Each structure stands twice: as C-alpha cells, then as structure tokens.
Amino acid sequence: IFWLFRGKADVAL
C-alpha cells in the first residue's frame, strides 16, 4: 500500500 501510494505521488513534480 505505502509503496503504491508513494509511487503515485512521486509522479508529481
């Protein structure tokens, strides 16, 4: 979960 949530936000600049 955390990994997926972090990956999504990471996309942002």
Image (spheres, rainbow, N blue to C red):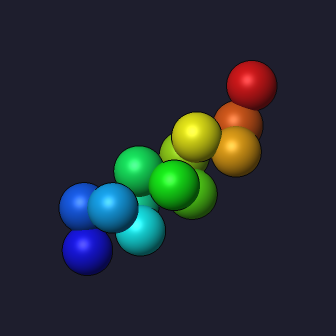
Q: Residue at x 33, y 61 (%)?
A: 3
Q: Residue at x 70, y 45 (%)?
A: 11
Q: In the image, residue 1 lies at what x, y percent?
A: 26, 74
Q: Is residue 4 above or below residue 12?
A: below
Q: Residue at x 25, y 61 (%)?
A: 2
Q: Is residue 1 above or below residue 3?
A: below
Residue situated in front as seen by the camera: 5 or 3: 3
Q: Is residue 1 left or right of residue 12?
A: left
Residue 4: which quarter of the image? bottom left
Residue 10: which quarter of the image? top right
- State how many labels appear: 0
* Residue at the limit of the structure toward the bottom, as seen here: 1
* Residue at the limit of the structure toward the left, as seen here: 2
Q: Is residue 8 left or right of residue 3?
A: right
Q: Residue at x 57, y 57 (%)?
A: 8
Q: Is residue 9 above or below residue 13?
A: below
* Residue at the limit of the structure toward the top, as seen here: 13
Q: In the image, residue 13 lies at what x, y percent?
A: 74, 25
